[PDB]
Length: 9
Length: 274
Length: 100
View 1 (cartoon, one colour):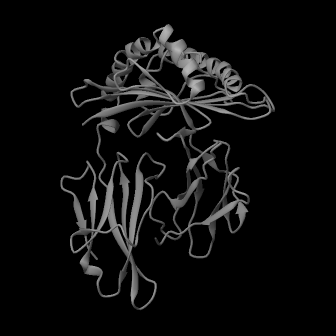
View 2 (tube, helix red, strand yellow; view 1 turned 180 degrees about the vertical axis):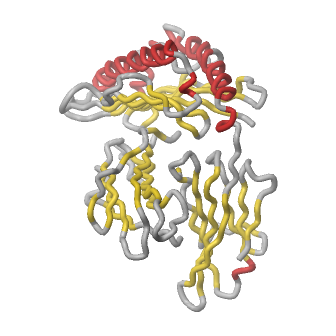
View 3 (cartoon, helix red, strand yellow; view 1 turned 120 degrees about the horizontal axis):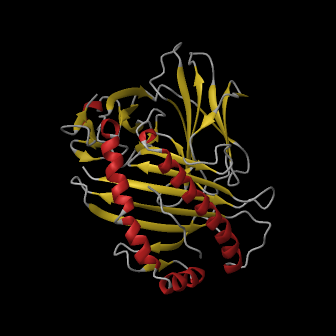
């Protein structure tokens, strides 16, 4: 299964 | 034996019409099972394997929520990176992300991965230890500092060593008939003369799964890299792979040459001769 | 800046039995950016029932796609694949060869 959130650069 | 789950995300900015295009794919070894396309009329995480169709509607609703959040973050990071590299709005740019995990034959965690790219070049990556980051350029160092301050490496590790391995373990049990399988290659050889003194020998490998294969030509039992052509492993389209390796030999010397075929679906590596 | 030129492979799903229903494949790999134009031709004319796989990439970040269409091989019809990319000044045509 995939990650909930993605981080900002 | 060992297995892997990988997620490949692509975000391409469209300076022309509309917001950036977001494509997401999910693989269990060499088999695709999920997909998300921002241009598609579905606007949901779509199944691409029959064994993933046995997941509940809460799974598909959750996975879609993650993909929407993934695309919106990618849309924001496209703008953030334009400023970092001092680029104009008229140019089309790409963000690529890779993450997943490796499990052993027993189902135990082996490796965790997290890698990002900007315009097909390394940007930021999580190290093998899953504690530190590798910043490719000066612009990536800005991101690295922000992620160190918010302890991002720990949050990525919790996913990679948790839900990621737990998901992969579940998929391997759910899709045992197709995923634990080892389809061996269907090997054959062709002989084609170019002249009366020269001939092309081509060794084939078809209908094999997984994609990992070795095709090595030998002359008197010594590896032949010279006067050889080895094409890239290619998908047949039915979940199986193809590969060939050809050598130009002098006419009459055909029997001095052997092709060694290594695949995990083979009990013993093959040695083919014309 | 670095742009990668695609690798092209025209082939059939199964060994081509002249007169028997099959799939004509065109594998494009090792390219950047993802924006590509891949056509399948029958005697120099584009087929319209062409489909393609979902966009994915290699460890080196280069993209790969599989384009496929239903086709019936014969020992008279000439099949090829037209590929256009920003790295190519002119479309590249690679003809299909079963008898490799």
